[PDB]
Every structure is written in C-alpha cells, then in structure tokens.
Length: 50
Length: 50
Image (tube, rainbow over all chains, first blue to last red; front, side, top):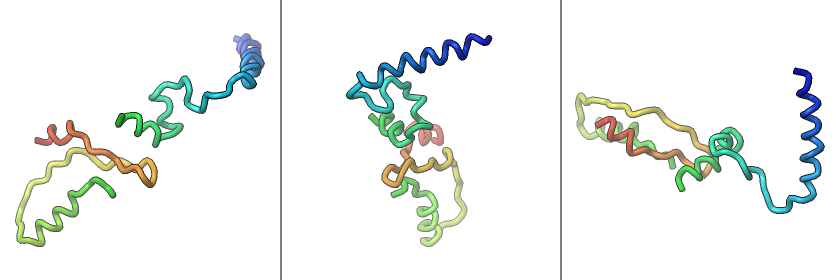
C-alpha cells in the first residue's frame, strides 16, 4: 500500500491534458452496456430493442 | 399505454357470466423507464406458462 495516492494524482494530471483535445465524444463513449443501466436507464432499454 | 391487460380482462369475464377459472402467473410488472417508454412483453415467459 501507500503507493496508491502517488499513482492516482499522476493520472489526474495525465488525463487533464486530454480535455482540450477532445471535440466530439459524449458521456457514454467507451463504456460497457451493463454499466450504463444505473446511469441512463431509458437509453439502456432502447439499445436492447435494437 | 401500459401493456398489461389481465385485470381488465377478468372484469369483462365476470361481467358476462363467468364462474371458476384458473390463474397462471408468468412474472410481475416491470417499471416504466420514463413517461414515453412502457415496458415490454417477452415471448419466453408466455411459452413457459403454457
């Protein structure tokens, strides 16, 4: 243990450079289908019909 | 509208002269995702009741 917080705030700065270079991707990009059911239930049920 | 019609059909049956009958449930109601998406009815539940 105790290497967690050192490796975490490195990630916080590393993905901080990615926010001015993304121009087209929305909320659910790169997510699993099972993990969006608590997030947006109406979108998850619509994908199941298609 | 809601896709469930069982309670309404039993009202029509007893009003037209029905007697004793058998009930086979296939599951319980599902919730609406929002105000314009009612739940769906599955083919595999109705054939399991048969």
